[PDB]
Picture: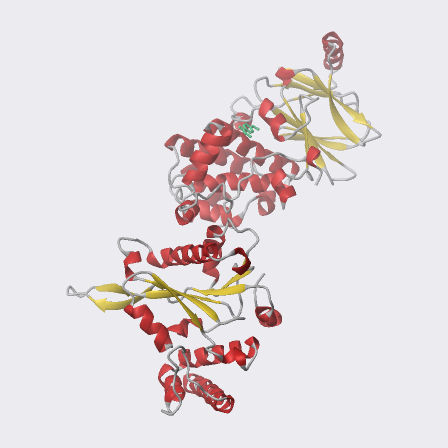
Length: 237
Length: 300
Ligand SMILES: CNC(=O)c1ccc(OC)cc1
């Protein structure tokens, strides 16, 4: 069924699973028209499909041309997501296909279920977790590749960089969600924390800086303070 | 007019004939039902006074043979039977009429209710849904499950309704996943009407038959089938104009006939609100929408 605080560790067992987040598939900027009306201009988007055990991130870039001449784009966006996830599964060898796909928003359940009718044995599941995957666009290297795309394109990343050499996927996922939660709550301050120290750099083949174990503890603390902070500024506590 | 004689009435029972019903007391001198209109299917149904568990009954067509009811004290129910000896049957019926031991099918002559509820119900088709080929009549009861229900357990005793499943490969063409799921016209018109049923009359036949089994026996799987068949039409952008008009009439008489007190368990809130207020055909069921809003405004 649904994924929540009680069955949280199933994410890190050895059954292949993918999270799918569609919150950055259809993106627009709202602006005024010369006649003083309002219109949208779409910009490039992405499907965020993540294996939480391995860190493998299948970033499918949604180029604005896919919306051209289409109606009801927020609804099409869910079906286009489901179409691309299904295409990805079909493209993978059988032993790499997921056993479960967990969607971060319940509106994706029916579109994905319909596009995956050919895989009756893949469980399509919702979650009650409020995961911060919408902030994936705050990771500079991911935002850059999406905005520069001139055509539909799939790009593969490992969102954990080399962390799994030193920590478990449970701890790596916990770090990732804390980073993304901070970037979603105060992007400016979050990025300030991550880059305040010019001596720590981001390797060309990584997304995040090359923190030592001890420096990650400092960073993780600073991110928690930020989230508590913004929580006070928001609610006046 | 035709007659369904009863050997006797040894147990107190509420007897139904189509939309009519009457109480018979244990060992009362009741010997059947006369003046049954020829030309329609009919259903004769039973609910024991002592165990309202199991409503059960028999669909039959008097044109297809001479049928009678006889209580079976071993199996504990009123059983329909065919009498092949035609002269024996006439002689039996005539004695019971002369002695006036029969209730008269009480049709008011203005009243087209039964015709309007059964216009498309074919008796040979019913034998297809309720498989028991040695009899010309068909037994149904409250607890019988449908072939689809058994997929999700005795197959001999199942209701073989047409399987409708909106998230099935049958309902969804590869490459039209969104189109076919949001507009079920392909599934209605090509898969079901052109492929399985052959024509709308056949489609209406199962739909009407599903309702009557839901209403008379409280058969839950029949009610699911009735709502599925409604929803497939209402969720289709492209439906022949003649089918929508007839659907409106069909549903109007079904809603009109339903017991007011049974609306809570026979009517699916989601399906009806969707059908009347959100679907492609939300504006095409004027008669049904008007009777639903005036009779069951709660559900909406
Ligand atoms: C099942 N296919 C059909 O054509 C059908 C037609 C009439 C009918 O009446 C009960 C039932 C089914």
